[PDB]
Length: 12
Image (cartoon, rainbow, N blue to C red; front, side, top):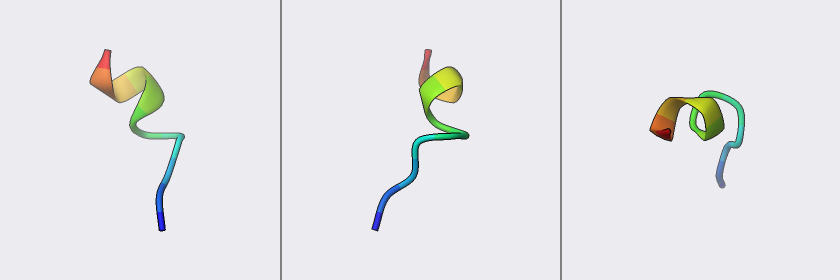
């Protein structure tokens, strides 16, 4: 129930 595509390079 999580993602690591539009958050990794989106959070920083």
